[PDB]
Image (cartoon, coloured by chain):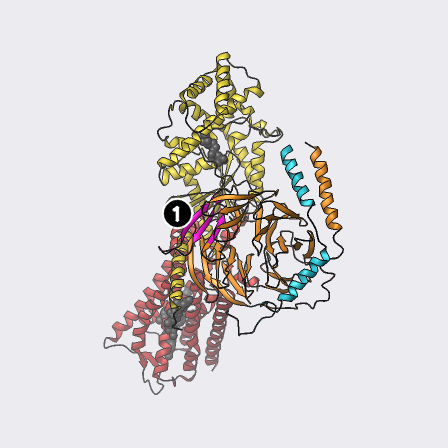
Chain colours: A orange, B yellow, C red, D cyan
Amino acid sequence: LDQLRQEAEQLKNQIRDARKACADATLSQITNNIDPVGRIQMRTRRTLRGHLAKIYAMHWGTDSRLLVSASQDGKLIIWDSYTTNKVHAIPLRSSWVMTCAYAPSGNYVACGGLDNICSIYNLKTREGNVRVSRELAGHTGYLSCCRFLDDNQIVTSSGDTTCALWDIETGQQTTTFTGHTGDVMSLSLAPDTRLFVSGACDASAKLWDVREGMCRQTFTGHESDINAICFFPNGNAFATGSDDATCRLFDLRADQELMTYSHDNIICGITSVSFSKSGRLLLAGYDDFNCNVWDALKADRAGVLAGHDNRVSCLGVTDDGMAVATGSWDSFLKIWN
Amino acid sequence: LSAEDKAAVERSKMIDRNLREDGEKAAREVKLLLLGAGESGKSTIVKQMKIIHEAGYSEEECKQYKAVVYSNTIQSIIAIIRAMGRLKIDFGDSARADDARQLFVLAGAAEEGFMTAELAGVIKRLWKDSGVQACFNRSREYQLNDSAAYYLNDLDRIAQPNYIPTQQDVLRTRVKTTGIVETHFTFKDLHFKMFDVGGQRSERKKWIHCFEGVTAIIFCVALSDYDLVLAEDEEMNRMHESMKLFDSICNNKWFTDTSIILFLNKKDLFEEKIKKSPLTICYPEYAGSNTYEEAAAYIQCQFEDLNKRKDTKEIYTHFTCATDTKNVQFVFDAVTDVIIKNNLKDCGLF
Amino acid sequence: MITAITIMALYSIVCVVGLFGNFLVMYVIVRYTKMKTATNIYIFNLALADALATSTLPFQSVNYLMGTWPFGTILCKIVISIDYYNMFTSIFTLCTMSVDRYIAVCHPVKALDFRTPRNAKIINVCNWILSSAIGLPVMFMATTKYRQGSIDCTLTFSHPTWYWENLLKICVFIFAFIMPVLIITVCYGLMILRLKSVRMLSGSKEKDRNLRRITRMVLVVVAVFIVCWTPIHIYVIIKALVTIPETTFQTVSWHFCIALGYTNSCLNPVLYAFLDENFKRCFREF
Amino acid sequence: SIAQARKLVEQLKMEANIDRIKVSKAAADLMAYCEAHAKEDPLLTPVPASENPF
Ligand SMILES: CN(C)C(=O)C(CCN1CCC(O)(c2ccc(Cl)cc2)CC1)(c1ccccc1)c1ccccc1
Ligand SMILES: CC(C)CCC[C@@H](C)[C@H]1CC[C@H]2[C@@H]3CC=C4C[C@@H](O)CC[C@]4(C)[C@H]3CC[C@]12C
Ligand SMILES: CC(C)CCC[C@@H](C)[C@H]1CC[C@H]2[C@@H]3CC=C4C[C@@H](O)CC[C@]4(C)[C@H]3CC[C@]12C
Ligand SMILES: Nc1nc2c(ncn2[C@@H]2O[C@H](COP(=O)(O)OP(O)(O)=S)[C@@H](O)[C@H]2O)c(=O)[nH]1
């Protein structure tokens, strides 16, 4: 009963000093010979207007042209980033939406929120407009993230402390990813789609296995709710943004902290992180009406993306690395280059 | 520039037109959020508002609500029988003890809402006992549903799960849906949007900013919970935890100026419980008399003194029974005041 | 001598401060705040009416300076048309702003489903159209008349000269002074009574002080309208009623009343725009 | 309770026996990936107006 905890503590100590014994250097000590990015300035090329309520999430497209955005007005607007157009506007059965997704093939769009149901939508119906294809029920908490593995599967985060892996056609949870001790906030999917990390309220990020279905690693270090998560482009690292006014880069191989991205005169939280194509830029959408541009190798601010009249809540970089999208609570999306 | 993609521009224009129409239709309404403690009467309040305004209920909806009724009767009789094992109240005779034994046996194997007539007879013979009525009277020493008398006084003689229950049965029973519950009704050219957080036992902080922009917060406080206690540590009060929950809601950063429609529910139980049990069980420093008016005003003034911004944020404390026609009129008056304030916020007036 | 320079000085100062106030309102309402609300569109169109109505003040002042109109018949036609049109527009937009505030207060749900920005747009368009419906006969009817070589321009009428004079005077009295002030007084009186009856404006010191602030600014609006429009209309009516001998004090008083009306149109934007809490909120951030 | 603690202990045992390469080689690999794709990154090296679709 109580004999298990006193040796779980020494197992934790074994993990901690095994990570400490494998930390002969840091990321910053061997990146000093790299010339810095400098002070890069990005301009708002497109100002996607048309929402009315606070946008909470957006997801890009694999073709790097279309994107989707979810807002409290109850609409899933599918934009056209090049021409500032709107190709679809899906009405939601429940207006309380906290996340949205987009298919790697571009055929489907997911959403979910306080109704605890992940609604999949089919954009290529020949019978007419976009209608609900499948409603994935089975979560007892609010859906907070959802990523399509492909047209067949989805990996969803929820506030019931458990993640999920739904087969869409059967509409059932094939695999459940439990192990956290807090409400799970956001999950990022690996480029090879075989693993995925997820942050939660317990200030920990867990790297799971998509096929096998177990937790492989647990990363600590934050002091508050981890709101955002994003894989590094090679799949061997990831960056988490938390409410403790800092971002941290972890490592799937060294299995410990790599670098913190903190700055003085910053107290607001981070709700979105996203990497560039080369991974040199870590874009973090803060809560002080801005979206700071960080360097993932020198841990210095190379820029800032101001122009939003409320809290930036969601980011995104296209698959070809061309642009940066930035939603906010001021009912506006923006594109940067 | 007169290209092939002009169809895309026309589609975007019609999408913008329809979306603007939907947005103005949404902005021509009023949105309210329900908050309160456990079993305070919020769902019954909005069910009454929906019944008197929108419509009744469907056949299949009444079917799952009768399933909820059967689950509620089973849970209530299980609690009221197992309360004797801790409160030490003996049965009238050995026949009722055998009836309780077979009730435990039947509750150990549950399939659906079949409601065998033997089980109904067991319920009837158990409820027709002096000890069970005594523990029903002494039920303030533990937890019990406030509609258990309604189930065990009228729904005992149902005899078959073959026909839909009455609207009163649906009104007093709520589902265990963990998701958010949204009800719509129209009262004098306003479209009300009640947002009951049914279940949602998840940190109360990652979606409390989703409601920054609601018109008002209909808080609910059970008046009959001043003498009841919680069977988890036996060191806290239900009224006191309702008070601190109201204090945490009122001091929230997202509801700095959001008006509160404070409903003090279950006055029909408070007025009949304050005759026997004094209010001094809840507040040990209460000095007034044990009358309904003074005690109710005392609870109201404590809940209003929880507010720290009384000069700008208004609280509408109304004593309600959750089965009243004036219940929606109180809400209408409060939201009309808030709409007047919002229409005064622009034009440089307020 | 002294009278000429005093009249020139007063017209010049009221024109420059009216143009300065209206253009400050213009720059603020196109750069700091936007016209996404109904009251901002009303303030913008009132600023247009007041700016274009006082833009013809230097022409009248130089007309009094030389006693002649060397500009021509076409320029005096457009000056007369602009003056009448952009004064009627200002009066009617004051009327519809008062109606808007009364609808916002006393009829809350009607203010929800009626006060869309597009509805304010169509109200302003109908306002300018209804002002043009009376400003265009004035365009067709005004002309340059020859009087002892001073070519002073005055509105000449049809063969029943006195009947058209009386018709124009009664139409500018009862449809631009009597009905506007009656509408303003009844709308603001009902608004003040409803704001007295409402719960969150009474029962405390701060709420009573707030209600005092709204009542004070409303009474300031009505008082300045009365004190700056009564001398003009009463003076015009009694001039049309009894003959007045020509003297220095008569012309000085006539031009002073004219200056009072133009001072009303001058201080209207500093009284509506710069007293708004929306403007204070958007300006204190700078 | 007991089963939950046993499951947590088994999970920590599964988390402790995995292999962990050095931080130096992983940081060098991240540096190599960054310098091997910095040529193709548009945000790092923005084309003025030629290949901008925006
Ligand atoms: C009609 N009445 C009694 C007015 O008071 C008047 C306009 C009177 N208008 C002024 C210009 C004028 O002097 C003139 C002569 C020749 C030229 Cl070339 C150019 C201008 C001719 C007379 C007004 C409003 C405000 C301040 C002062 C006067 C007004 C009232 C209501 C609606 C429209 C106009
Ligand atoms: C010389 C002048 C006085 C002649 C008459 C000018 C007319 C045509 C002008 C003056 C005021 C103008 C309006 C002022 C304000 C707005 C709001 C803006 O969002 C759209 C145009 C709109 C609705 C304008 C339409 C045209 C308008 C009515
Ligand atoms: C007197 C107070 C209370 C109110 C004043 C406002 C009105 C009634 C005033 C303003 C200007 C005034 C006029 C100014 C000058 C003259 C010329 C004089 O030879 C006779 C009186 C007469 C024609 C005045 C009549 C009254 C008048 C029209
Ligand atoms: N006799 C009587 N019963 C009342 C009254 N008010 C409320 N109740 C009952 O109290 C229980 C909890 O209600 P509810 O489901 O909303 O709880 P909750 O949403 O907080 S979880 C419901 O069964 C209500 O019939 C009243 O005046 N008289």
**Farthest bottom residue in view:** C149
**In terms of depth relative to the viewer, which is nearer, B327 or B254?**
B254
Q: Residue at x 56, y 24 (%)?
A: B141
**In terms of depth relative to the viewer, which is nearer, C154 or A108?**
A108
- For this view, does B314 lie left or right of residue D24? left
Q: Position of residue A116 (x, y in %)?
A: 49, 44
Give ligand 1's quarter of the image. Answer: bottom left
Q: Position of residue C264 (x, y in %)?
A: 44, 67
Q: Using the image, name the chain to which the residue with label 1 belongs.
A: B
> In the rendered image of this protein, does residue B292 appear above or below residue B96?
below
Q: Position of residue C191 (x, y in %)?
A: 42, 53
Label 1 lies in ligand 4 vicinity (Cβ under 8 Å)? no
> In the rendered image of this protein, does residue A207 appear above or below residue B111?
below
Q: Residue at x 76, y 55 (%)?
A: A24
> In the rendered image of this protein, does residue C29 appear above or below residue B172?
below
**Farthest top residue in view:** B93
Verify whether residue A94 appears in magenta: no
Q: Position of residue C240 (x, y in %)?
A: 32, 71
Quadrant of the rendering where the C terminus of chain C is positioned: bottom right
Which amino acid, by three-letter code, is at mark 1?
Leu
Verify whether residue A115 appears in magenta: yes
Image quarter of residue A278:
bottom right
- For this view, does B334 lie left or right of residue D44? left
Residue D1 visible in image: no
- What range is drawn magenta here? A109-137
User: Residue tagged by mark 1?
Assistant: B190
Residue at disc 1, secondary structure: loop
